Length: 271
Image (tube, rainbow, N blue to C red; front, side, top):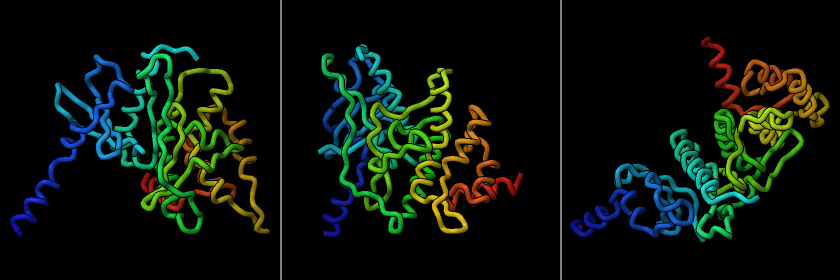
């Protein structure tokens, strides 16, 4: 009985990676036959990417919970980028804040991007503020790396509140059609602008939620001072100019997450 209880706990302590790779193999839906670095499995209604090296499973990441003429290889290269994004986020400790899908390439005549679904509720400013701050800082970490959400805050004048949700543990963002955006090297003005907006995306989300107010308690149109500064500092983001970010903050023109203001000040203190 203590015996039987020790036998149950032992079965449960089996390393999870071994259980995952004996699940349903979904790899042909997302990667082609001769690829040998990743396999994709569904284990107990959850879909995982597993990294391999010489037939041995090395690492795994949980991607989601289950319920225009390009070649298939074009989309498979994107999927390999997304899978590497998942592991990159895991070892930055922020992967759980993002619900990312993949291009389904099973049928060459019906290639489609699966946007994973979730059981979750909309966020609420008063109740969820600690989780909101935690998510916004995770998004800034992603933005700092040069990646951004394609439909959350395209610029200071755009917001998609429906793509933020809360579970009972945390706030996540969803519905990234085609995955993260990033710099592809184009030099037209719109791409130059989008790069700046992508670096500062987290700031737009935060000030949408917690907009600053003036001496009369009216909402400040924080978008105007920011857009004016972008105009006079082309190809420059506030996130890459922390001293300017903090000056806007202390003038009351933008809000910042408490921990970010703390950390930026402590860094400047020690330099």
